[PDB]
Length: 425
Image 1: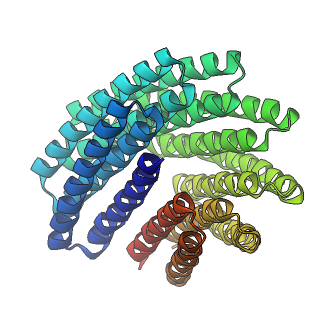
Image 2: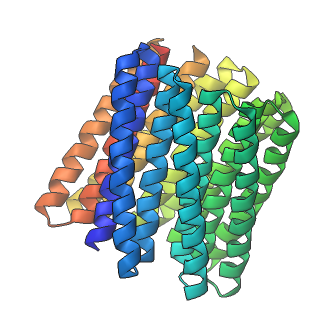
């Protein structure tokens, strides 16, 4: 759909504003933050209007992707509230996050009733991202009451995501089950950040427990999907596992428990090995979309590794994660080059996304290791952006509008990696 295509483009625009807000933090520019705040408001309104049009037509997936775009916009607003130090900006972001949350929660209930378990899971992703925006808005506002509100909403999404996962697993909707576990994992991240905001190590310990549970359910789905030869479903399950390990690493920071940090690093390495393995099998079979999705999970796993190195204060662990990020980056570019030569521009665009996420991991690992590596991550971020720009151009010339939009997401993610690298610089 033109509505799905529209929603993917808005997701790309919303991610780019996140990068501008991060750039305002690194440079300390209050004027850039206000500019980013204004851009986030406009994008949020565009996403709301797309969601309204999509729901009226009955397109539940397109409406769900639009609400994700809206929720990412609120995170940009929240982030901007930090760069500006404007507590009224954070309070405005807090209310927009609740609005998006309620729309997404209602959208999930409607999709599940109609049987659209995929739309329901994507709707729950929008809700979980909205809760992350609320928890960040709590940090920006210094409001432990908003943080507690985020914590309660995170448990609600996690509960519903776990419910939909078991419902989707019963009828054999393995892709819907895996996407449901992605929402659950993002919900645990939101709970972990809410624990940092609330300064509650008890909530942090709870987030660590839930992250281990989502992780365990994700590996169950990956094993079942793999046995049946459904490599795309198995790859999406590994995305959920990798996001769960990110939640655990953040929870370890919130709890100040280096034993959880070392455990996250262990789980992150396992996901990394499973994803790289699944990518090789898909590549031999020519299933380049599955291979590209697997390398997204690999790139997210290295992010968890880098954050686990921050939680452990281990500069040697940070250097290893940096080198692993460069490895996943090169594999992703291999999948993209092969995909572009065959004309599978969606597989190429998905692989471009994996490459840009791998540069985020390199940038975060450079921060943990402490400046020459940050400069390299910065330059690698420019290169990933350029590779995604070429893919978007080739896709448009091939008449593949959705692949062009997926590549725009890759461009914006590379811009986030560039901004994070600028923080270290």
